Image 1 (cartoon, rainbow over the protein chains, first blue to last red):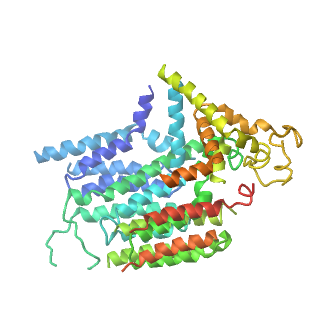
Image 2: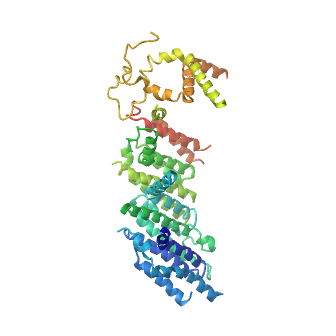
Image 3: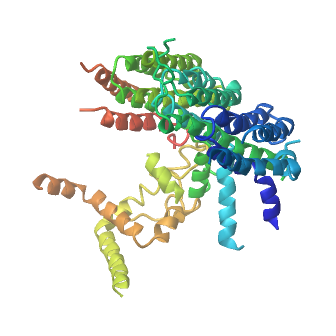
Length: 369
Length: 109
Length: 47
């Protein structure tokens, strides 16, 4: 019975759903944090150790003990309280009793042809998920959408001070992600008590958390996204712990395909960034994009790729600072997402420029004649 | 079957188009066979001129060479797809030969 | 010559940014211009 061990491991997500029903119930503030977001912060704990992914058991052990204490003290309504948190305490106390290991002390770091194809495809995708393709791009995409295009003003700490500097300099790309989890956890904690308590209308572009559901409805989406990325990362981190460059090119069509699927941005990235700057220019047409366009001219009059490479750290700096300014101009938008895309792309090309670089004949007939 | 009939007619068409381009085709065998190429891959060309003009009166013989670097290198994939692809190949050869007539047609159209 | 054509395209887009019609087609041109400028190799295009 594989499901026996699968369900002995299945307790983190099982608790998550019960903490989702603990959310929007009991205490609008306390309950949500203590249960859901402290389990989400314990997720962050093991991720921030960068070595103890799903191994931290000390704090995860006392998470249960904290929840038992709450139930013992307190949790229609007497009965409601009881039933409701017993329902989650039942599951929690069960981990403490037995099988705490499979999820916390076991998954550690220390049919036929069609089905065969299916599982291979699962793993190639996950390889790209453990690649920068997912580790970063998709995460920051959703971040920008749910910060700039969504609740602005105070979510700058979740974007323009984080990803606007983490994208160019990838040294702190994972640290930034962990800090992000922590900060949006903090943001939901704060908006939990809305803002309508004795309002007497300090200034940071106060939008005020007036709705309940709708207002709590996006920050949690990116919190979960961080978690999902971390899951697929640590999955293949332990799958690697335990468990053609120009040669395929001249082979055939499959060879050409393979080469480029693996090495697009490697070579095309610079031409890409140039065209991404044009995209920003067109989806804005303001005075702010004259700056982007002026930089475009500068790096295009540098011709030889070696000269563009020494103008690249300054270009990436400009882009990052511009995203920050754009927020501080919207606080103290869709244009912000466009400048993010340009930043993301050019940042990846800065991480290639001075790093990684330092029948099919009929197809070649077309492009090459 | 209707499909099978169309296939045969496509091959009939290729033949007719080749008959039209015949003279130009043979003029492109005494010249363009040792001219246009674009198949050499990898880096650059070592024996630059020997790898083109000196490779492999209207209808000449083996005055130059035989078929040393594969005469049928081009005719590999060309004849490989004798259906479909070759119809369009024959079309191009016709309009390359009769480009003067193509111009005239366009201007009166 | 190709680089000057690239600069023409750039200036069209950059002057349309300072308006007071669209850059869509000029961006398609930019892509193609950049593609060809790039494919002027000293290897495959040397052939």
